Image (cartoon, coloured by chain):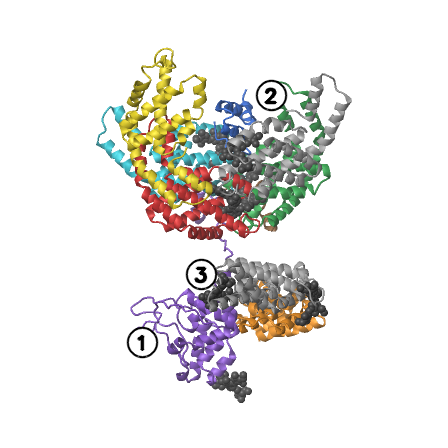
Chain colours: A blue, B cyan, D yellow, E red, F green, H brown, I purple, J orange
Amino acid sequence: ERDIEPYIVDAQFTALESKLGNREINMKEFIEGLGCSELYQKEFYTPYP
Amino acid sequence: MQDAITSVINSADVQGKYLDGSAMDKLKAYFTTGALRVRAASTISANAAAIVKEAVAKSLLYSDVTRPGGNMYTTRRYAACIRDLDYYLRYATYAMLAGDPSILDERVLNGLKETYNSLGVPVGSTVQAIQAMKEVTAGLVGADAGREMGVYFDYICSGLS
Amino acid sequence: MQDAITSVINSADVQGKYLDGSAMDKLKAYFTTGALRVRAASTISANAAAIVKEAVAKSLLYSDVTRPGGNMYTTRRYAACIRDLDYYLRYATYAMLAGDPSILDERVLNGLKETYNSLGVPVGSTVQAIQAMKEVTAGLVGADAGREMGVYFDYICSGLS
Amino acid sequence: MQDAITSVINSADVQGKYLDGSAMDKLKAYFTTGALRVRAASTISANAAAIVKEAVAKSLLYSDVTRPGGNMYTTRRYAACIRDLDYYLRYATYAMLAGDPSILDERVLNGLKETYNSLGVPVGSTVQAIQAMKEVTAGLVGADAGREMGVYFDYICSGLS
Amino acid sequence: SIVTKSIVNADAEARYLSPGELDRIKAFVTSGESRLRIAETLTGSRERIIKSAGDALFQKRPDVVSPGGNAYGEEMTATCLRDMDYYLRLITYGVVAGDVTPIEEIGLVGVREMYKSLGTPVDAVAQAVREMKAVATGMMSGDDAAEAGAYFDYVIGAME
Amino acid sequence: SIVTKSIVNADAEARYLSPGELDRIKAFVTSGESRLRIAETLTGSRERIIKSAGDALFQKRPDVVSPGGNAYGEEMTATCLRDMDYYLRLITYGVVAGDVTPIEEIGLVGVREMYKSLGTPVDAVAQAVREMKAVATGMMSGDDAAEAGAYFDYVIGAME
Amino acid sequence: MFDIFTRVVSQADARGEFISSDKLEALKKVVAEGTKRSDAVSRMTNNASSIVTNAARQLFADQPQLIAPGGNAYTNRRMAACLRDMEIILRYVTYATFTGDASVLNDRCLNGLRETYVALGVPGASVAAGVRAMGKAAVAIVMDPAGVTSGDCSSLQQEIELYFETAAKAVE
Amino acid sequence: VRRFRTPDRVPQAGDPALFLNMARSAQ
Amino acid sequence: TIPLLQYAPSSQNTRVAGYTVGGDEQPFVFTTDNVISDSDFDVLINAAYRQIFFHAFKCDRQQLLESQLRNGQITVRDFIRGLLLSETFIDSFYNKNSNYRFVEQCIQRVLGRDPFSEQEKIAWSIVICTKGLAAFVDQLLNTDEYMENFGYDTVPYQRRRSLASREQGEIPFNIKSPRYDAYYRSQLGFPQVVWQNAVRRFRTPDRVPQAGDPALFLNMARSAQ
Amino acid sequence: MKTPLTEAVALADSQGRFLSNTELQYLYGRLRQGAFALEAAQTLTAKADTLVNGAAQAVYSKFPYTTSTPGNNFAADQRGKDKCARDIGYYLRMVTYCLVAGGTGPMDEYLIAGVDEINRTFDLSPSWYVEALKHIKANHGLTGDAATETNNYIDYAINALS
Ligand SMILES: *[C@H](C)[C@H]1/C(=C/c2[nH]c(/C=C3N=C(/C=C4\NC(=O)C(CC)=C4C)C(C)=C\3CCC(=O)O)c(CCC(=O)O)c2C)NC(=O)[C@@H]1C
Ligand SMILES: CCC1=C(C)/C(=C/C2=NC(=C\c3[nH]c(/C=C4\NC(=O)[C@H](C)[C@H]4CC)c(C)c3CCC(=O)O)/C(CCC(=O)O)=C2C)NC1=O
Ligand SMILES: CCC1=C(C)/C(=C/C2=NC(=C\c3[nH]c(/C=C4\NC(=O)[C@H](C)[C@H]4CC)c(C)c3CCC(=O)O)/C(CCC(=O)O)=C2C)NC1=O
Ligand SMILES: CCC1=C(C)/C(=C/C2=NC(=C\c3[nH]c(/C=C4\NC(=O)[C@H](C)[C@H]4CC)c(C)c3CCC(=O)O)/C(CCC(=O)O)=C2C)NC1=O
Ligand SMILES: CCC1=C(C)/C(=C/C2=NC(=C\c3[nH]c(/C=C4\NC(=O)[C@H](C)[C@H]4CC)c(C)c3CCC(=O)O)/C(CCC(=O)O)=C2C)NC1=O
Ligand SMILES: CCC1=C(C)/C(=C/C2=NC(=C\c3[nH]c(/C=C4\NC(=O)[C@H](C)[C@H]4CC)c(C)c3CCC(=O)O)/C(CCC(=O)O)=C2C)NC1=O
Ligand SMILES: CCC1=C(C)/C(=C/C2=NC(=C\c3[nH]c(/C=C4\NC(=O)[C@H](C)[C@H]4CC)c(C)c3CCC(=O)O)/C(CCC(=O)O)=C2C)NC1=O
Ligand SMILES: CCC1=C(C)/C(=C/C2=NC(=C\c3[nH]c(/C=C4\NC(=O)[C@H](C)[C@H]4CC)c(C)c3CCC(=O)O)/C(CCC(=O)O)=C2C)NC1=O
């Protein structure tokens, strides 16, 4: 919902972005991998029931 | 979201009338100022980070808000402040290009007061930061382009206050 | 994804027996290596950026790759190169901590060969850069853990070639 | 995605030199073709539906494909066929405008072969339809731009076969 | 160029090219001589531009030429001028392309990451392209200086 | 901290704390005394750490203190000493908490964006934390220096 | 025009305090090796003529154009002037190893020499090959010991190779 | 005296002005 | 030995005739024969110093040549020769400049004209390194142009610098050519930046008082009772 | 730039002749000089701070109207005495440079060429620096050959000033 850059110490999703660059993965699994890792969980899962 | 052309067309359409001479004169005014708007938008797109960092160096640096206890204290809060000021400059550039501040109250000033009041963000300090951003960009692009930037900067400061 | 412990448990599990004394021998071998594995991992995690910059400054910098005509010419390709090297070093550190190169065969060398053929990446320059990084990390963290990193870097090179 | 201009810049970039006079020669060749390329592109954009309907009426209509037993029998398959033909014509127009068939190799012929094998689409009927469309657009827009469309339609057929 | 960008725009919107952007390609076609003249004058005086801009940069920001800085020594200063050569070369490519996209493809994607690797301060590079812009627009006639300064302005905007 | 991280990691998984995580929390609870001793060692001698680390930094990287350097004019060096004091304070917080979520969650997330907006070379800041680590691990016993150097190591790693 | 003693002087003056002790160990060992230095220069100097003719003889054996008609050193005064230039470069590199600093070499003869040889039409790479061969003979003339006290003359062989190399690279 | 402005106090925590002495002391 | 290169002359205000008339742009001419009072020797010696050394200080002045010239055994041509071979000229002009720039400066100051081309300075740069500064100055003085324009008894000047009905004629050559160049100031390392801009004091930014502020009425309350 | 080596190069250079035996002697005669000269430069570096303080004491005791009369040139206040410490430290440092180089050229280049106009326009009486150099040459306490070199040395300084 925001620009990701003030929430990342470094370029955090470079593995999934590089896999999308080869298109060994699709955009939907990239969306699911964005949902699965820890920035989204510390963003939208922690302060809410 | 509408520029001067779309607002003129919307007024003439809500009337149901054709475009009379006053609408033609308004569109001629916009079509004369548009080249200056284009050149000022290019000059502002040149120096986004410089205008933002000069606005912080004028207003927010070395004050209490960057000290402990201030709302601009941590690196997360500093990065979010730079992000918010970049948003204000970018949307002021958009409203300068359109010639209508409808994008500002559609997409900046919509829930901004309630967001800043829920977070604890000082509204006066960010209004002073936007005013210094306006002063810096009016020093950048000249007198009249600085004025037509400052009308939308004053729109953002008025809707924020 | 298996450790030395998980590979021992797996091997004792395929044949179906319980833990024998030779498995305990391998486990104590893993632990007495694992203490210095931890300290070497902390040292590599502390100095990863300097290790990668010394690796590229050793081998790739004044060649035709970082020059025009090579696959490392543009800033896009340079950033991809530094990212590839950082990933090799990070996965070598994971394999050093686990005591098993199954992670390198699992996540690194899975489809890396065919995309390196398809993008036209030179295998030899990458292998030289990894070996330069190998003795850079060997001179950094020490001799025995230098050998530890050495067989895992060599595993990456053998899967690459 | 590269033009004649972007391919010239790319070729001068891989070897690493600046712009030589032969590059300027290729660029002026591209421009003096590009004016009539624009007019032919406008003519093709104006008459695309008639071009496609004349192409299918020339070759595919009274055969076994548009009849039962063919891959063009149902209205689903007919609509997919007309859409495939429209896409061939549109991408041929893009390749004609750019002066380079890299777009046809990039977006059209990327995985079109294997899905045409897997769905059971006849390659020969498609090639006949494309060639019929080729001389339909040649008789429409003229001789030299007919040759321009001809080599790009032939590029599509060679990537298909 | 402008034609590749109009083609990928008509492709993503899945339609033919509009007569507005056909007129844009035609106007670009007619303005080819002016952009050839601009790139001609820039390829003529590249050494003088680089020498004056590098000395102006070293006069403005002495951190890079100081001991402990990035561009310290003969070879490091020569590589600094080589990077300015690459950026002026991409400026000429984008000037003759009519678009900023070859400058984007060749030298704007990962410059922050690679200069984060080398240790180069990127704002110093932005100052270097600023001095190259000031010198090249000082050389050109004012309308052509505005055209070249648009691409120079885009490069320093993508820098900082 | 450790307890926050274990609670959150069991919390997403919709399970209780596993017994291995529980003896992790127990071992951290027992090692808290040595953590507090390292924290008093780092807290009580902050003046000499900041002073000697600033001295060794400006000896090592003189261009930032040199004309044209970001840290120029007594207040620029002095101002930098405040940023070094901030990072030593976050080091003490991370030493007590047993994990780097105080350090990362306060002063390492947008550090690149902030120091790019200020015009600061981040490698020289990494050298500042390196000299702080040298003075601090020169001040303690062996295992205490290793446990503090882990967090100093994390800060220099999160810089680059 | 700079002696290495006044190199230390001018550097300490631009610093602005007294000469430190480490520079004084270095200058004392300079004084202990300057014996080698000065008469290394004169050893290089004595056969200077035979060195010059041997290097030119080798150069015109390697490049037969320069004594062919139409070449740069073909006519008699141009050939004599080329011998004059090679003697001058040897003499100035001899001055430079006598001062102990390459400042006299880069200051007195090399600097405008590049532009002079380009504007005259004179080849520069031929001069570079000549000064390189001349330097090889120069150390060996100064390195081999015949009727001389055994001494550490190897230090000069290093620095005189550096001086000839700077001469050849600055000619270009 | 009833000053209408902020009290004359200075050198608050996390201020650069407090560390300006130590900035002077270092090279 | 080897003679000079033959360099073709180029066009200039000197090799042309010119129809000169008494004005001030014409340099005041200082001649040994008519100065015969003790003060006019001081003016002549000052003028020759202004040409050769550009305002020589008391350290640069040579007592022997001035003494001997006031007696009158020395000719001013020999006095200029003694100035050029004196060590303050060698130190200030032959040391710091290369041979080509030295010949440029010395031709300007002895002959009173710019050299015709770069190849002329190149052709004259053989003789100074092969035969010494004394032979260079001697061969310069023996040439017929110096003799026809000045002679034995005349301090040289910049010749025909300024044409009639011009605001400017030409740079006076004392301004144009100083003793350093860019190459040797690089060795001395002089452009150390003055660095008095953008020091960035860290103290908190001043904010202009808002309307209705208590302070606004501070300045009048200080003036009031 | 007067060292014996650069003057040998200038003679050979002015003449155009190649290096000769006459030039060579200077180098091993610079041994008679330098074998004490570098020692004396080090011991002057050690003696330096008390030398400037004693020279300031001697100049203030010789001329009390400097410390009494208010003026820009006179050292009435602190900053004038700071200028005096700077000036005598410059003189002592040029003596040390002149001692290390072997000739008067550093001292003649860095001090002597402009001292007449500076003493004329800025109202600095040179007898003050006469007092300072005489106090230095009395207080330095050099031994043997090194001491003799300084007297020739420091007397040249006074002769340039007087
Ligand atoms: C230090 C050795 C290096 C350096 C420092 C430097 N810092 C600044 C200015 C600021 N720094 C901060 C930093 C932080 N605020 C935080 O909350 C945290 C986490 C705890 C950090 C790291 C901020 C907010 C400022 C702005 C002023 C303020 O303190 O409110 C400067 C001045 C920059 C300027 O433009 O004036 C300097 C010079 N610079 C170096 O060269 C060293 C390598
Ligand atoms: C495009 C229209 C738009 C705007 C403007 C916008 C603002 C916005 N600013 C925010 C935070 C912020 N905004 C600020 C800014 C300031 N605080 C200060 O002290 C200064 C006076 C001022 C900056 C000049 C700070 C410090 C935060 C972070 C608050 C926190 O992390 O607790 C947040 C909280 C969530 C998040 O950081 O990412 C939003 C949604 N969102 C929008 O969609
Ligand atoms: C976790 C395991 C893993 C790895 C290693 C990995 C690598 C990987 N490397 C890539 C590219 C690359 N890798 C390199 C490599 C190099 N530069 C050179 O020339 C040298 C030979 C070498 C530097 C050491 C280059 C140049 C590219 C980009 C080429 C291009 O597509 O333009 C790409 C394509 C997408 C991208 O641009 O990054 C992937 C997916 N992906 C993974 O998931
Ligand atoms: C066309 C796109 C493109 C870019 C941008 C590019 C950059 C580039 N810059 C380099 C080095 C460098 N670039 C700099 C430049 C700078 N540091 C300074 O002090 C200055 C402020 C700044 C100059 C503006 C320096 C000092 C190096 C050498 C770094 C090192 O050797 O560690 C190198 C390494 C040498 C080589 O392989 O040529 C590359 C590839 N190459 C490209 O192909
Ligand atoms: C103090 C330092 C100094 C140098 C080095 C110097 C060089 C110098 N070399 C010259 C000519 C020359 N130089 C050469 C050189 C060579 N012949 C070849 O074929 C080779 C490429 C090369 C031998 C290495 C030749 C043939 C000439 C005569 C060209 C001419 O005079 O027409 C001339 C023109 C004057 C003349 O001699 O007729 C100068 C001034 N002058 C200086 O004052
Ligand atoms: C101008 C009259 C004159 C000469 C000739 C002279 C030569 C000379 N050569 C010396 C030393 C030396 N000379 C040499 C020379 C060499 N050793 C080798 O094995 C090399 C092959 C060769 C150089 C190529 C060495 C090695 C020394 C050792 C002592 C030293 O470093 O001076 C010394 C030191 C003092 C002494 O020997 O009593 C003298 C006197 N001194 C003079 O006053
Ligand atoms: C290298 C050897 C050399 C010597 C010796 C020499 C002497 C010499 N002494 C001169 C004047 C003078 N000589 C004196 C001498 C003296 N005053 C007296 O009352 C005493 C009788 C005597 C002092 C011993 C005076 C007063 C003048 C100035 C007369 C004048 O300039 O009008 C002049 C006229 C130039 C001038 O100084 O104004 C010369 C050339 N020139 C030389 O080149
Ligand atoms: C490296 C060689 C060198 C010399 C010789 C030198 C002399 C020199 N002394 C100066 C000032 C001074 N020097 C003195 C020292 C003295 N005056 C007295 O009345 C005392 C008796 C005596 C103390 C021994 C004072 C008081 C000034 C101050 C002039 C002023 O403030 O206007 C100045 C003016 C520069 C300034 O304003 O700081 C120069 C150039 N400077 C140099 O760089």
D57 relative to E114 in the view: left or right: left
- Mark 3 belongs to which subunit? G
Judging by the rendered image, the residue that carries numbered circle 3 is: G121
Q: Residue G153, located in which quarter of the rendered image?
A: bottom right
Amino acid type of the residue tagged 2 in the rendering: Asp
Q: What is the x, y in percent for residue I74?
A: 47, 83
Q: Exactly how many numbered labels are in the figure?
A: 3
Residue A20 relative to residue I12: left or right: right
Q: Position of residue A46 (x, y in %)?
A: 56, 24
Q: Give the mark toward the camera: 2 or 3.
A: 3
Q: Residues within 10 Å of mark 1 (few under 14, many from 20)?
A: few
In depth, the one of I45 and A6 nearer the eye is I45
Q: Disc 1 sits on a residue from what chain?
A: I
At 31% from the left edge and 76% from the top edge, which residue is drawn?
Answer: I22
Q: Residue at x 61, y 23 (%)?
A: F9
**Mark 2 = which residue?**
F11
Looking at the rendered structure, whether the residues under marks 1 and 3 are on a common chain is answered as no
D132 with respect to J75 (left or right): left
Tag on residue I216? none
Q: CA distance from mark 1 to mark 3?
A: 46 Å
| Residue behind label 3 places its C-beta within 8 angstroms of ligand 5 | yes
D35 or E86: nearer the viewer: D35
- Indicate whether I83 appears above or below A44: below
Quadrant assignment, res J62: bottom right
Q: CA distance from mark 1 to mark 2?
A: 105 Å
User: In x, y percent, where is residue F157?
Assistant: 60, 37
Residue neighbourhood size for the residue with mark 3, other residues' Cα within 10 Å, grouped as few (<14), some (14–19), many (≥20): few
The residue to which callout 1 is attached is I22
Asked whether, in this view, residue F55 is left or right of residue J72, the answer is: right
Q: Nearer the viewer, mark 1 or mark 3?
A: 3
